[PDB]
Length: 82
Length: 38
Image (tube, rainbow over the protein chains, first blue to last red):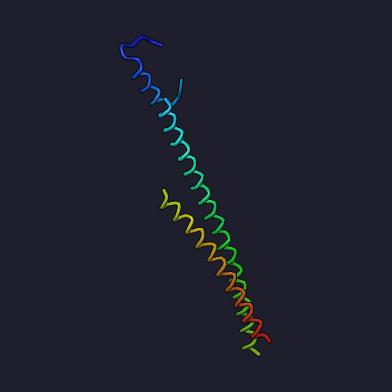
């Protein structure tokens, strides 16, 4: 609004530091940056969730393997005793 | 970021395949116990 000696450059710089509007190239760059950041965050969250689920599955299957090894050891002991 | 994502995905795949290997080893141990019992 104000009558600065050089207004357009100052206005566009304050738009840069603020990031809002009211220019197509700046809008395109900002949209691309936001989309890339959102995609990276979503991919990282998905990878972390997949890692956690895989760790849970590994622990459960390790439990199954331990139980089966226990059964095998018990059977071997029973056979050896007899 | 790509390297970190690849590392996380590969760790998840490794854990899942370790789960599969543990399940198969459990099946093998159960089969061995069944064979020994008879």
